[PDB]
Structures are given as C-alpha cells and as structure tokens.
Amino acid sequence: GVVAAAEKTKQGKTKEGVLYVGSKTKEGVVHGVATVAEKTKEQVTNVGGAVVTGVTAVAQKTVEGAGSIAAATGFVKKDQ
Amino acid sequence: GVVAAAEKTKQGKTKEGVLYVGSKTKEGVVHGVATVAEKTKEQVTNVGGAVVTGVTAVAQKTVEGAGSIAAATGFVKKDQ
Amino acid sequence: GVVAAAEKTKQGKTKEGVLYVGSKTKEGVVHGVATVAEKTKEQVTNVGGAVVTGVTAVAQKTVEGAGSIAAATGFVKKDQ
C-alpha cells in the first residue's frame, strides 16, 4: 500500500511586494534535470510540481495546494 | 505500508517587501540535478516540489501546502 | 510500516523587509545535486522540497506547510 496523501484542509489581504532579477552574461549553458545512463532496465521521471530552467529561471508561488506523488519501481517476483 | 502523509490543516495582512538579485558574469555552465550512471538496473527521479536552475535561479514562496511523496524502489522476491 | 507524517495543524501582520544579492564574476561552473556512479543496481533521487541552482541561486520562503517523504530502497528476500 505505497500511498502518499496530503490535505491542505483550510477553513478560513495580501500585499507581498515585488521580485526583481537581472542578468548580463556572455556564454551560458544549463541543464535542468538530466538523466543519462547506459545499459539499464527502467527509467522514470515523475514531475509533480514544476520544473523551471534557463539562464534566468524564476519560480514564484509555485506549488500551492496539496502535492501528492506515489512512485513505485521494481518489485519483481521470480521465487520458486 | 510505505506511506507519507502531510496535513496543513489550517483553520483561520501580508506586507513582506521585495527580493533583488543581480548578476554579471562572462562564462557560466550549470547542471541542476544530474543522474549519470552506467550498467544499472533502475533509475528514478521523483520531483515533488520544484526544481529551478540557471545562472540566475530564484525560488520565492515555492512549496506551500502539503508536500507528500511516497517512493519505493526494489523489493525483489526470489526465495525458495 | 516505513512512514513519515508531518502536521502543521495551525489554528489562528507580516512586514519582513528585503533581501539583496549581488554578483560579478568571470568564470563559473556549478553542479547542484549530481549522482555519478558506475555498475550499480538502483538509483533514486526523491526531491520533496525544492532544488535551486546557479551562480546566483536564492531560495526565499521555500517550504512552508508540511514536508513529508517516505523512501524505501532495497528489501530483498531470497531466503530458503
């Protein structure tokens, strides 16, 4: 029973402000989430929330609510 | 019973402010989350929250709420 | 029963301020979370919260709420 529950059981003014980023570069190479392999059997990539990538990559108020992820890999049975 | 529960059972003004980043570089290479391997059997990458990458990578108010992640890998049975 | 529970059971004004970062470099190479291996059997990377990477990488008010992560790897049975 490999489960994963999450409850934001909320019952009951926002004036946050700003966010500012600046960038000035010459050369840039970025790899966010890379899976490189050779001679494997299984490969999984469960993205529940977000994935944000780049020389300028911001993530504001990204995952509100309830993030739930089950993940099961393998579980072989060759007995007897 | 490999579970993982999380409850933000909230019942009941925000004036945070700012955030500022600045950057000026010449060469830049970034790898956020890399999985490199050779001759394996299983490879998993469960992203529950976020993944933010880059020469300028910010993450503001990212994972509110309830973050829940189950993760099971393996569990072989070849007995008798 | 490999579980991991977390409850932010909150029942019931914010004027934090600012945050400031500055950067001026010539060469930069960063690796956030790298898993390099050879001749293994299993590889897992459960990200519950966030992962922020870069020559300028900030993380403000990242994981509120309840962070929950189960993680089970292995558990082989070849007896008798």
Image (cartoon, coloured by chain):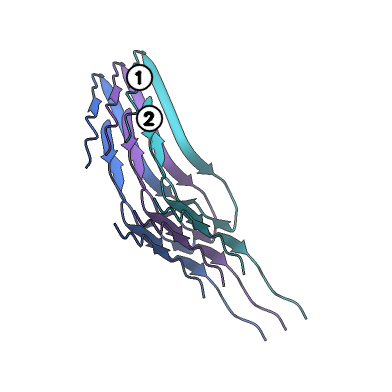
Chain colours: A blue, B purple, C cyan
Tell me, yes or no, if residue B21 can be seen here: yes
Q: Chain of mark 2?
A: C
Mark 2: give few (<14), some (14-19) or many (20+) Cα within 10 Å: many
Question: Up-down: is B9 above or below A15?
Answer: below
Residue A38 visible somewhere in the drawing: no
Task: Name the residue beneath numbered marker 2.
Answer: C58
Left or right: where does residue C62 sit relative to residue A26?
A: right
Between A65 and A53, which is closer to the camera in this rendering?
A: A65
N-terminal of the two: label 1 or label 2?
Answer: 1
Comparing C18 with A57, the one in front is C18
Q: Provide the chain ID for the residue under circle 1.
A: C
- Element type at mark 1: strand
Which image quadrant is residue B32 in?
A: top left
**Type of residue at label 2?**
Val
Return the residue at label 1: C21
Hey, what amino acid is under mark 1? Val
Spot occupied by residue B42 in the image (x, y as percentages of width and height): 51, 61
Going 52% across and 67% down the picture, which residue do you hit?
A: B3
Secondary structure category for the residue under label 2 = strand
Report, in whole angstroms, how far the alpha carbon at label 1 lies from the one at label 2. 8 Å
